[PDB]
Image (cartoon, coloured by chain):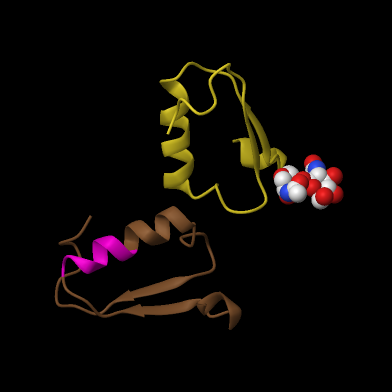
Chain colours: A brown, B yellow
Amino acid sequence: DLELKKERRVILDCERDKVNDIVDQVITIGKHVKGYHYIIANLGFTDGD
Amino acid sequence: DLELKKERRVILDCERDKVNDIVDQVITIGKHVKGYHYIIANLGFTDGD
Ligand SMILES: *[C@@H]1O[C@H](CO)[C@@H](O[C@@H]2O[C@H](CO)[C@@H](O)[C@H](O)[C@H]2NC(C)=O)[C@H](O)[C@H]1NC(C)=O
């Protein structure tokens, strides 16, 4: 549904558990290619894999 | 190094073990995006994940 508007910039605002699920979903879909930018809005950045 | 020749079609000819590692490496480097075509040269295609 986000692909209809051609939106490349995504901002993630969740805890240390949902961010891993979103990352795994992006990996399975294939959105981590050069041309995107994610923002993990949380106090911890290196906590997740 | 393969990206230098601008080659997108890759033919995989390995057992049921190396193909999984190659698929995992492709997933990690983000080459499974639309625009590539892989060929698994083996009798068992549904065997691997
Ligand atoms: C399947 O992957 C191949 C690899 O690019 C593509 O199929 C090509 O399909 C187009 C569309 O019919 C043809 O014009 C080409 O001749 C095909 N062969 C190539 C490009 O080598 C396509 O990206 C994918 N989908 C289909 C339906 O083939």
Q: Is residue B22 above or below residue B18?
A: below
Residue B8 on the magenta span: no
Which SS does the magenta portion mostly show? helix
- The magenta region covers A16-22
Q: Residue furthest front?
A: B46
Name the residue rendered at 49%, 50% in the picture.
B30
Q: Is residue A13 above or below residue B15?
A: below
Name the side, left or right, on which B29 lies relative to B10: left
Observer-nearest of B31 and A1 = A1
Observer-nearest of A9 and B45 = B45
**Which quarter of the rendered picture does the C terminus of chain A lie within?**
bottom left
Give how far across and how far down residue A17 sits, in percent.
17, 65
Give how far across and how far down residue A47 sits, in percent.
15, 62
Name the residue rendered at 25%, 61% in the picture.
A20
Give how far across and how far down residue B1 sits, in percent.
59, 36
Q: Is residue B11 above or below residue A7?
A: above
